[PDB]
Amino acid sequence: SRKKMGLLVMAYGTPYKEEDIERYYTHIRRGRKPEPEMLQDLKDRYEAIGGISPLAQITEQQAHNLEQHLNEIQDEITFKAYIGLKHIEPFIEDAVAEMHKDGITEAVSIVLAPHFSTFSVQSYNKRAKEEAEKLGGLTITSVESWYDEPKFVTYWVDRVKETYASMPEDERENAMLIVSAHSLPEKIKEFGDPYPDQLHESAKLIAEGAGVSEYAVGWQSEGNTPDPWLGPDVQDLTRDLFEQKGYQAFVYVPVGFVADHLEVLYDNDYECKVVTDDIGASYYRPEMPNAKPEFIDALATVVLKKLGR
Ligand SMILES: Cc1c2[nH]c(c1CCC(=O)O)/C=c1\[nH]/c(c(C)c1CCC(=O)O)=C\c1[nH]c(c(S(=O)(=O)O)c1C)/C=c1\[nH]/c(c(S(=O)(=O)O)c1C)=C\2
Ligand SMILES: [Mg+2]
Ligand SMILES: [Mg+2]
Image (cartoon, rainbow, N blue to C red; front, side, top):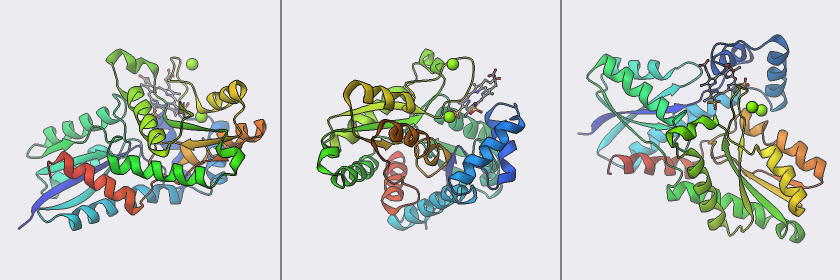
């Protein structure tokens, strides 16, 4: 009775083992293999956050859980999840090829990043649809952004509320909320890319919902290319806000990210933490969505809304 549909889940990607680090970063750096010192640095970063292998399992678990949940919450469509990654196998084109091989003719895609950008989301979507057209007989409808899905906003609002609620009286009254996503080259502005606007909307929505009056928008994890790169970077923003107003606690909500990967566990929980430790402030970073039922239900709602269901 049910309509068979592909569920194409797209993400940045993460190495599966320490031995994947070289090729993963080469790919991110557009063919420029890291020198031995940087490679070792990277290995040490992964070791410090507790290993690489758990990290890559989250994306699999997200996709699996989302398929299962969508299949249970409605009765018209049977979804089959396929993972398509930007920087490591299974690549986006691999996933689309597999769907076509498997007799999928109709699919919905979603990127595990809630904000639209020309660099990330739009590129993934183009690549997916281009491989589908190349093979023929397979259409894909693509989610573009979902940062404003009420269930997703509520996820973050509730975590933020719990964080503040757990603070001592003096910290709660003198805290700063820093809402962040992955930095991108500043040149996206020439296309009128709404990515920066969507992050400030995300921050607005979360702060408003949590009853947080003092918040700021920051960027993190920028690459090293000759052009900038959206700023301010969270490290610089943290110190600057402290110098400006003396905040005693900083709460990091890397809303651009959906899971416990290197950008959060290292770029917040180490890099921002060094800064908060230095200035004498408490560090807080609520739990990432990961594969949690509340988050999977938000994603389910996003997918079905896109389908008009
Ligand atoms: C060393 C290097 C990096 N990135 C590039 C280079 C070598 C080219 C040059 O600088 O002349 C180059 C690019 N990154 C780009 C683009 C459009 C280029 C130009 C490519 C060309 O035409 O040659 C985009 C880009 N890049 C990154 C992302 S994002 O993570 O999805 O946000 C995106 C969208 C990520 C990184 N690129 C990096 C690094 S890292 O310094 O940490 O090793 C990172 C974390 C480094
Ligand atoms: Mg960095
Ligand atoms: Mg620069």
